Amino acid sequence: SPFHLNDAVAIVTGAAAGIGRAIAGTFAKAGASVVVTDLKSEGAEAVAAAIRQAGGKAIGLECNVTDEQHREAVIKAALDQFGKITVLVNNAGGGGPKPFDMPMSDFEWAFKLNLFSLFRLSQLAAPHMQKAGGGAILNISSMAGENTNVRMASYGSSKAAVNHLTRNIAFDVGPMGIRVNAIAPGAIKTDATPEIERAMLKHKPLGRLGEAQDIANAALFLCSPAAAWISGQVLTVSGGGVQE
Amino acid sequence: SPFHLNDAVAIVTGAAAGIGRAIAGTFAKAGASVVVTDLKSEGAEAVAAAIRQAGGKAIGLECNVTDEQHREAVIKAALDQFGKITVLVNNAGGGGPKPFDMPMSDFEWAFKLNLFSLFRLSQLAAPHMQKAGGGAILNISSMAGENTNVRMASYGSSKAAVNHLTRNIAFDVGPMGIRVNAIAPGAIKTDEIERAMLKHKPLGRLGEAQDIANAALFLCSPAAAWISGQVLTVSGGGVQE
């Protein structure tokens, strides 16, 4: 099997819940050593701990991906505790529908949060990846990056920039043996009601919502050697459609 | 762990050599019974026999995908042999650079060979896929479907049809629990100034068949049960024309 993460150190940000938590769990059971990360320090340690009492190796620390000190702490915490870095999964980000006349800081924040942070983490992890022979970067985008709609000024165009950064920086980091891709996930069952759900699926050909595990398998594939030759790709994982 | 094709029956067309050979072989070790198909009947039989003696189940068939009688034979041959069909890998297809003043028979052929055949084979397989509890269709496309260049009038736009058909029939057969995806492969070393492409492939390397087969295996695996209407380009991070 090439879908395993043997001898790998993976940093996973925003991993207290949902996708990033499943990516972190999934990357551990594939035999990677995980550095769980989140804005909320309790949540990072909850997931890093449950990973350990289930067999894997994992530490969890607080990280505000927009704080340059918090970023450098994660890089160092991973090297200090595991020796190398081979996988960076940039799952931290946020935002959503805002009016066009939104205050400028709202617009600028979306780019600090969704783009400036993960570019910088990649800039830090890249030379350590290079020393370890190579590695894989994965950015969790959003479907608003390739769609067009109302109230999407900051969200949809900051996630668009994530997509195009991914397509471009793979040229920069390929020579160093780094692959860079992105998943754009559909809507995931979280709620942690039936009629507003049945309407959401009116445009999802496969007829169900997503599971965090569904994103984690794609994250797995894209970060394993099974995807040794895939870089610069934006893979949409949404049951064939769009929602909400 | 979710990356296996257990209790699956996969038709792989154009699988005597190259990408389709690798796919067929990969799919067998992953647990699928495989219906190996190619224009050359005995080329397909040699692949099927290797899978069998390497431990798998498989048969090999002559099939011209452009001929409706063959298409039906292969579909029936899969059912008589294995009871069901759950995976269809539309890999056969041809063509390449052509002058703009080409004869219309060439233009039309490219669509007949790269597009109509795989849509027809999709039509024949969809009902059996639904009776079987679900399945996946994977179309082997080409980066010429999104690239633009000289001499690509027939090849580039037939393959572009394959990409959007993929995206569009995903809506149609999703309600039948069928996923439809495509792989656009780049420069695969199949069979000196080679260094041309390499000067535009960020990962410093051409592709092997198994690269394409790994992505194939993923997209037809339960690890991708919620992925559909996708064109995953597998090219080393760049473009090679």
Image: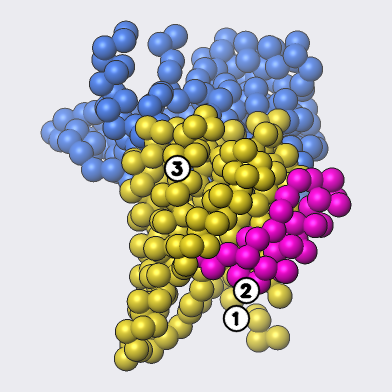
Chain colours: A blue, B yellow
Residue, disc 2? B198
Task: Calculate the distance from the C-alpha at mark 3 to the C-alpha at mark 2.
Answer: 40 Å
Magenta stretch: includes residue B227: no
Mark 1 burial class by Cα count in 10 Å: few <14, some 14-19, many 20+: few
- Name the residue nearer the viewer: B213 or B40: B40
Q: What chain letter is assigned to the residue under label 2?
A: B
Q: Is residue B91 left or right of residue A168?
A: right
State whether residue B223 is above or below residue B183.
above
The quadrant where residue A25 appears: top right
State whether residue A6 is above or below residue B92.
above
Residue, disc 3? B126
Mark 3 or mark 1, which is nearer the start of the sequence? 3
Q: Quadrant of the C terminus of chain A?
A: top left
Mark 2 burial class by Cα count in 10 Å: few <14, some 14-19, many 20+: some
* Helix, strand or loop at mark 2: helix
Instruction: Identify the magenta region.
Output: B37-65
Name the amino acid type tagged 3: Ala
Q: What chain letter is assigned to the residue under label 3?
A: B
Q: Is residue B174 left or right of residue A218?
A: left
- Name the residue nearer the viewer: A155 or A130: A155
Marks 2,1: beta carbons within 8 A: yes
Q: Is residue A15 left or right of residue B45?
A: left
